[PDB]
Length: 115
Image 1: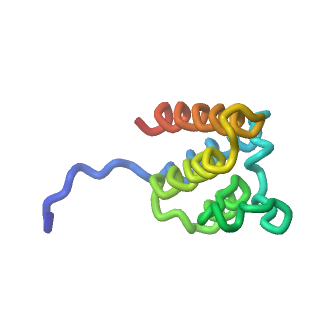
Image 2: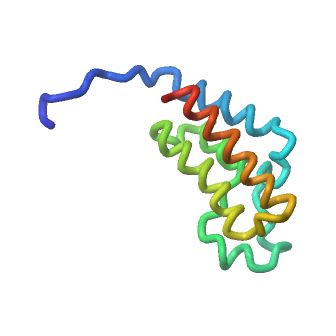
């Protein structure tokens, strides 16, 4: 509360560390469904159904331009990518499996780097 604070967690490396995680997600062999925004002209149903599209290139641009106020807003967009994938793709599909795999890969790196 006013003039009463928990000890200051060092957040000075968060930007660099989120960048490194994002690099590792970008280079994973199962990243291909997530590298670029879904083409809303060429994928029937996507625009209407997925209210907030998100992809790794969009996260990269947001990260590089100071549009993440803190490491949690960064995690929320990464998770959004996988939540969107699950919304639109059957579990038993190459893309559906890719999303599960990437979400797992992310959540481990997230815990190991920050928890």
